[PDB]
Image (cartoon, coloured by chain):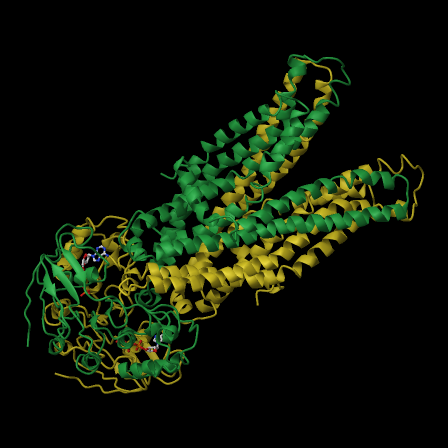
Chain colours: A green, B yellow
């Protein structure tokens, strides 16, 4: 599928439509000072190309004061040739920084659009590692594009000037025997960069699946070392490593032919200008002199045609770094393609709803005629895998019902409806950010300076000994918030998140790892004290005093609304 | 700290001691066919450098049959110049593959040594992203080393031959004015590659912390999208992105000077051979002729000294790709340094044990006089964060007691002692591998062909409907085993892992998200039926019928051994 086709150009142009969004952008005005910099350095390189030629004239007669103006002209030209070549290398690397800022942030608006970070990771197998496409492949495309962004910018000009310099030396049978050397030179690459990209996207999945294998160790270091699983996870990660090293070694077995088809074009290009001028030795249609029509004509013709291929083998010298780019735009363009179409009182109403697991066909629950009002706070207890949570997912817009109508009558927000997941979430950030987490900032939201509400609610949830652990509410705790915290207090920090953003309906789920009558009840006592109406999931014989309904689910689609008292 | 010092060489040589382990290795014998390949191509490049010179002689007299042997000699030399240059580029990229196979697998033996994946990730802040050092920085060091492994291998020779060619043309005042141009040329880089590496390791932490930020989204897509946290995690990940893009842009502001100090050395090197021969125009100690001693002497001297700097500016042309290498060996050498010193009946005995959290000072538990025998299976119930699990960590060798003596009298294994973590673990692999997980293979271990034991235990744990979900016990399920599974059946798959590897002592922990009398008791009924003696953690009013002791922990170090009946 990633086969360098005519599809790749739309995957490349729609990438380039956001790298360069419009004229007078932060990249096009960095590109115009890239064109007008290699244009200036092409004048200087030729001008410093004349300095050793006009050096023998002043050394050939030994006048130091007439020499001191030449070196001073040369050294001024050298530090002009440097700071034009160095600023050519810099503003490409400033373009590489300002490309991946404009492409990742374009991908971030697509990745966190509504729920597209959810659906790619748990509901899609076509797009394997979207973390690797956004982080590394944008970094690796924008580097391999910027390395060839200094030679794809002067080659629109230095090919034009040298073809004019060649047309005035050979004629109609001149540069079209070099343009025909490009058409043969790039067809022999476009059929040879084929199995590169097919073995590079496959090299990029396995370099991303291996990196995710290490972050199934870094995120899960605490459970894995309980099993003493060093000698297991070695033979699991090396199995992930060898599959990468048997497709990185496979890429070099394919890129060997790409190195051949470039080095053949380069070195035979040093002699193909000479066989253009086989027309004396095969035809001789302008045969006038043996030492003068033959010598210093072809020495004038090879001095201009090798001068042409010197700016024309550049476009094939980067066929490796365009096979790399075409490998990465078949990763990023595989991602923003699937992200673009993916962008397309009385808590909730459920009308004959038939939720199933996404892989299988049988429904987890069969028919729902469900309605939640203020002060109801129904339990959703049941069996182990009967789809207790799968009701809650379609309330959060996670899944869609196969056959049924689901809607909510209250908006998501602080005082609206707030979910709590089964395994809890904690982002990187301060303790102040871990509790207002769906709101991400509170001082423009609230306006009140004092945040004594959360310092109340932390001790009200009981974990005020954590505040001394995180040294106040300061930035960059440098924690993982998963291994350093505790599932006893992951729930309590999730409850302080719920207590801060007290809704008209909480969609609380699995408040376990807390004492069933001592603090599981006490965390629920703040719910009626704040008027929360928490629709909860829990198979514990303490929740029924807080909950009106029961909603058993024992079976492949069951209803059993009980209203215990 | 990463400042290109004399420490860096020991961090580079101890890396190179394992890239090249000994002579006749899989890399040194790939390096000897790299030396003996650029040596062969240096002869060919000079031999094909004579083909256009001896071309005007046969074109200057128009003999096609005497010409047809030249092009046939040339094209044979071109396809010899290609497949020596291309095999030079290939066997470097085969060296890059076979370097990162030998360096990652050296790092994997250090990473999963005893518990070093645990201690780096949850007990260390000095080594931030060891996933990025092992995966990406070994890949990025071994690529930036292999790109300069084709020019650091011929430069021991082509510098020798050209200095001999220069000593026979200028003398004592010749190449030591070029060797002095290297000593100035590399001191002006060794003081300029300083702030590159200091801003590249900092560029590599933030490129690794950002990639881990995406895998705190990919691993946690299910809880984060319950909060509708797209508009939050955008402004969290972009905050992680902008900190990378304000230090990648900072690197280009520092690498601009490194591009200057190379392009100044290169282009002034085109004229510094000429100012070596200021000794006619300043001294004139061999002044004999004006047109003949002055011309075609320096034209012979610039034809050999620029010929020398052509092989001598290569060693400074790669000062960028050695600033990159020195950035990455201060990442890998920061890692294998901290990994090398890190390598240094009656279940357990606890003698006055005073476990604390690693950051704080106060002990979670104060004094332990504890002993576990067969058929005891004590509960460890208590408060939410009083260090219930912290007793279990030192039993697994995770933590060490601050003051106390801990030991075990039974080895870890199938029939020995087996832990279960609070949050459960599932590696990538088949369902057969998810249940024998601390053993990683069973058919050399067991020998028996039929594995009806696990198909018994899965339905005995109840989750035999999972076997149809994973299509048998086949390889590469392509799942995450965390989002696709369920915390109801994460426990049940952990229990089938415990039932397969039935120990004399299970160190079970938090068998929650299962029905307290229906299947939490039923999973424990297989424990006495298999004779497991499971020391467990759980604050539920059903576990006490299976458990002898209680071991309350209500407070900052408490004992309360009760032995309920
Ligand atoms: N994201 C998913 N992708 C694919 N299959 C899934 C996914 N989530 C769940 N499933 C499948 O469908 C079932 C639904 O389980 P569900 O989410 O209802 O968990 P539960 O154990 O009932 O709830 P809880 O653990 O919160 O008590 C899972 O056991 C699994 O087989
Ligand atoms: N790996 C760690 N690094 C630093 N601090 C830690 C780490 N693990 C725990 N802590 C700190 O020490 C405390 C010890 O908690 P512990 O592991 O005993 O959890 P618990 O809630 O008692 O157990 P459980 O959740 O299994 O019932 C944590 O609350 C936290 O403050």
Which of A394 and B214 lies nearest the eye of the viewer? A394
Image position of B184 with respect to B495: above or below? above
Image position of A15 with respect to A256: above or below: below
A261 displayed left or right of A448: right
What is the residue that sits farthest to the right in this orientation? Answer: B288
Q: Position of residue A79 (x, y in %)?
A: 72, 51
Q: In front: A318, or B66? A: A318
| Residue A449 image-quadrant placement | bottom left
Residue at position x 70%, y 58% from top? B187
Q: Nearer the viewer, residue B174 or A422?
A: A422
Residue B172: percent from the left, percent from the top?
83, 48
Residue B497 visible in image: yes
Count of all numbered marks drawn on residues in the image? 0
Query: In what quadrant does ligand 1 lie?
Result: bottom left
The quadrant of the rendering that contains the N terminus of chain B is: bottom right
Quarter-wise, where is residue A440 in the image?
bottom left
Determine the image quadrant of residue B565: bottom left
Q: Position of residue A294 (x, y in %)?
A: 73, 18
Q: Is residue B447 above or below residue A320?
A: below
Any part of residue B151 in sight? no
Residue in the picture at 22% in, 72% down: B510
Measured from the top left, where is residue A81 in percent x and y?
70, 47
């Amino acid at each position: 599928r990633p086969r360098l086709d005519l599809q790749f150009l739309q995957r490349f142009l729609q990438i380039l439509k956001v790298l360069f969004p419009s004229w007078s952008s932060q990249n096009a005005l960095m590109f115009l000072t890239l064109l007008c910099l290699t244009l200036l350095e092409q004048f200087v390189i030729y001008q410093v190309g004349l300095i050793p030629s006009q050096y023998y004239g002043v050394l050939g007669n030994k006048d130091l004061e007439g020499f001191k103006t030449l070196t001073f002209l040369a050294v001024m030209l050298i530090v002009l040739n440097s700071t034009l070549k160095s600023f050519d290398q810099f503003t490409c690397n400033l373009l590489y920084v300002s490309w991946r800022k404009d492409l990742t942030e374009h991908l971030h608006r697509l990745y966190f659009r509504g729920r597209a970070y959810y659906t790619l990771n748990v509901l899609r197998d076509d797009i394997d590692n979207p973390d690797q496409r956004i982080s590394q492949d944008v970094e690796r495309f924008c580097r391999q594009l910027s390395s060839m962004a200094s030679k794809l910018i002067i080659s629109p000009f230095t090919l034009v000037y040298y073809t004019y310099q060649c047309f005035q030396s050979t004629g109609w049978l001149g540069p079209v025997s070099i343009f025909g050397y490009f058409i043969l030179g790039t067809v022999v690459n476009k059929t040879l960069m084929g199995p590169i990209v097919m073995k590079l996207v496959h090299q990029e999945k396995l370099e991303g699946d291996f990196r995710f294998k290490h972050m199934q160790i870094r995120v899960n270091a605490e459970p894995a070392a309980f099993y003493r699983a060093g000698h297991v996870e070695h033979m699991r990660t090396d199995r992930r490593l060898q599959r990468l090293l048997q497709t990185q070694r496979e890429l070099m077995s394919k890129e060997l032919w790409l190195y051949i088809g470039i080095n053949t074009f380069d070195y035979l290009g040093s002699i193909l200008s000479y066989v253009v001028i086989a027309i004396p030795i095969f035809s001789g249609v302008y045969g006038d002199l043996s030492p003068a029509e033959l010598s210093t004509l072809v020495s004038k013709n090879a001095f201009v045609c090798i001068y042409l291929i010197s700016c024309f083998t550049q476009l094939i010298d980067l066929s490796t770094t365009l096979s790399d780019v075409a490998g990465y735009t078949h990763r990023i363009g595989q991602l923003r393609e699937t992200l673009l179409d993916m962008s397309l009182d009385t808590a909730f109403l459920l009308e004959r709803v038939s939720i199933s697991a996404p892989s299988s066909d049988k429904p987890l629950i069969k028919d729902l005629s469900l309605k939640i009002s203020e002060g109801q706070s129904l339990l959703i207890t049941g069996n182990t895998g009967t789809g207790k949570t799968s009701l809650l997912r379609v309330l959060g817009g996670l899944w869609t019902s196969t056959r049924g109508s689901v809607q909510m009558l209250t908006d998501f927000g602080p005082h609206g409806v707030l979910f709590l997941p089964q395994k809890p979430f904690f982002t990187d950030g301060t303790l102040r950010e871990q509790v207002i987490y769906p709101l991400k900032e509170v001082y423009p939201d609230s306006g009140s300076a004092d945040d004594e509400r959360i310092l109340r609610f932390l001790e009200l949830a009981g974990l005020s000994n954590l505040v001394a652990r995180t040294e106040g509410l300061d930035q960059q705790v440098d924690w993982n918030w998963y291994d350093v915290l505790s599932p006893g207090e992951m729930q309590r920090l999730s409850f302080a998140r719920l207590f801060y953003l007290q809704p008209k309906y909480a969609v609380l789920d699995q408040a376990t790892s807390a004492l069933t009558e001592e603090v599981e009840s006490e965390l629920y006592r703040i719910g009626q004290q704040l008027g929360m109406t928490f629709i909860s999931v829990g198979h514990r014989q303490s929740l029924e005093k807080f909950h009106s309904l029961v909603l058993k689910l024992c079976g492949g689609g069951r209803w059993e609304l009980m209203r215990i008292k």
